[PDB]
Amino acid sequence: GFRKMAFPSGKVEGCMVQVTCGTTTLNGLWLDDTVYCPRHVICTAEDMLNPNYEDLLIRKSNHSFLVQAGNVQLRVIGHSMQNCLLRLKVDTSNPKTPKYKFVRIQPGQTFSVLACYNGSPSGVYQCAMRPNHTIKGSFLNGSCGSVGFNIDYDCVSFCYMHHMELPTGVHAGTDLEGKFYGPFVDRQTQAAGTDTTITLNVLAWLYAAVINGDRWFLNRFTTTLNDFNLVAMKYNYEPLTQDHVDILGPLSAQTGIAVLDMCAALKELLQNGMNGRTILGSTILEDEFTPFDVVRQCSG
Amino acid sequence: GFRKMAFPSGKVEGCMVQVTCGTTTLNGLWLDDTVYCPRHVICTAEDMLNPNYEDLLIRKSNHSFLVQAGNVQLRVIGHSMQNCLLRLKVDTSNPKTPKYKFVRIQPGQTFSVLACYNGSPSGVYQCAMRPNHTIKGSFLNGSCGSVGFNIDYDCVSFCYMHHMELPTGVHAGTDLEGKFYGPFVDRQTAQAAGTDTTITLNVLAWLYAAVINGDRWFLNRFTTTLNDFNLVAMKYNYEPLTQDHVDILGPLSAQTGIAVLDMCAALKELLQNGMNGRTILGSTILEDEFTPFDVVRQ
Ligand SMILES: *[C@](O)(C(=O)NCc1ccccc1)[C@H](C[C@@H]1CCNC1=O)NC(=O)[C@H](CC(C)C)NC(=O)OCc1ccccc1
Ligand SMILES: [Cl-]
Ligand SMILES: [Cl-]
């Protein structure tokens, strides 16, 4: 059937460390001879509301930072700031460093999160970047510096590092260049925009239904992308982009259903409703399975 | 902030290997100097409808089994069969072998699945052992020999090895002693499970979760006795709750200040009146694959 499934976490487990300033410990990512972690490890409680990160970092030295892999200290030999991350140079290249890249994902894309506490991995789950640049994650005190990732063959694409929980319970963080997703800032003040449904992934869900023989919702009509997007917005669905259309290409080819023809099917569902009928066993449309997920779980 | 979470899979990934016999390739589990895998790797399509496994295995040699750890061949130096599993002895010990044990899990309990293809880990997800001894997994051709596990500290407790997809799309397999969960058999036939039931203890745990994450519209001012709850539960194909189960829910009851039987009263109401279209923790339906431990652990 269809499960939310994460990528195997071993290659990322091999990169997790803890970074401590004073009594403040969060997680870091050790790749070759660099450790990446959220810059607010250098904050005290009283700096959190409006920290002056440049001045806080001037007061630090290499020997202010305790970096550990397990209980083994990793000596810090340089430190600098890159946007909202610290880059700590260490004197040991991580022998478990996988093939990796740093990627900045788009809203709607999914990734696996390895939730870690004190450098120790606790659990792994899949989540989607919401259109408002938050994730609906599962993060407790001590989770900061946990990362999100995807795996392509042997290569780990790191896409997320965790920094904060917003008042509504959703989560915000950065890419591995330290740039936040969305408008958020790493100070202890912030509201996410109203969220919307990830149209790309609903379309993927419809394609998945068709692949599995559930196709009552197809119709004989089509739409333009503009007409679809104008309707979608009235129902709090995200507008489709050209990238979304391209990403649906494989599923469209697999089923023979043009992307804009599936858009016409979805438009009719939005305007008329499900009327009690179901799709893949549910009255509600799923929006956190990507086209990649559908193809992986339908075809392998 | 509450998701289905799997255990980190690294300690298990380091044990996964590919096993080939004849034209059949599936996964095995390499612990110390032993590789475990489904015995139907020795079957030919014809054998499959009524395989006399002892007779088919005595006709194999050590050299019939090709075991590969990545790019490296492991030489098989012996083999035995234990229920529905083969135990292949190899000439190399796995240095990545974690501390581990073999456990037979009980219906209602959860575990993580590491789905593997050609000895290569592909995905990880959480599963419950259903009351009818199936699991609702995500398994394709090539997934046989994938394993399910839990982690306690740094000890991996292996509880599942994958063998079968039933016509209904659910899945069936064995423990790591090779004994099937459920009435299933490793012959190539269409098999049906007994009727399934809902795991009441897990639904209650998940309702306590919803109350910890702020959601509590389904609560009510009423209570019930344990037996009256079980009468209604059984009518709706829910498992009855034992006093042991009530005891297990204590900490969640303490944390939230909601007595277990008060939560039972809320569930009874949900069973009899439905959700009115509302949702709990985002779900339109009552989730039953979170245990009390799973909820507390997160
Ligand atoms: C499992 O044997 C496997 O993955 N084998 C490797 C392999 C390689 C290439 C092609 C096929 C298989 C397999 C796992 C199944 C397949 C699809 N999803 C799964 O989870 N298990 C089986 O094929 C069972 C083997 C028996 C001997 C245990 N057979 C099975 O599931 O049959 C179900 C069935 C349904 C209707 C009618 C007859 C049989
Ligand atoms: Cl049969
Ligand atoms: Cl009733």
Image (spheres, coloured by chain):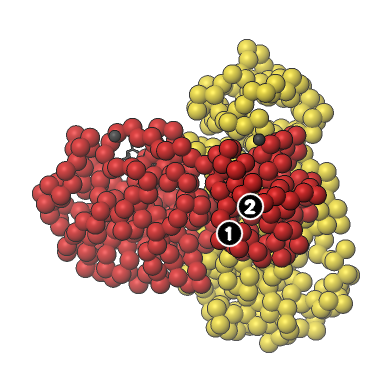
Chain colours: A yellow, B red
Q: Nearer the viewer, residue B76 or B265?
A: B265
Q: Residue extending furthest top?
A: A220
Q: Residues within 10 Å of mark 1 (few under 14, many from 20)?
A: few
Residue occupied by mark 2? B226
Q: Quadrant of ligand 1?
A: top left
Q: Residues within 10 Å of mark 2 (few under 14, many from 20)?
A: some
Mark 2 CB near ligand 3 (8 Å cut): no
Question: Residue under mark 2: which chain is it in?
Answer: B
Q: Residue at x 54, y 24 (%)?
A: A214
Mark 1 CB near ligand 3 (8 Å cut): no
Q: Nearer the viewer, residue B186 or B75?
A: B186
State yes or no: discs 1 and 2 in contact (Cβ < 8 Å): yes
B115 left or right of A78 in image? left
A19 left or right of B134 in image? right
Q: Residue at x 68, y 73 (%)?
A: A26
Q: Residue at x 14, y 46 (%)?
A: B56
Task: Check the image and report above or below for B146 versus A229.
Answer: below
Q: Nearer the viewer, residue B70 or A281?
A: A281
Q: Residue at x 58, y 71 (%)?
A: A120
Residue occupied by mark 1? B243
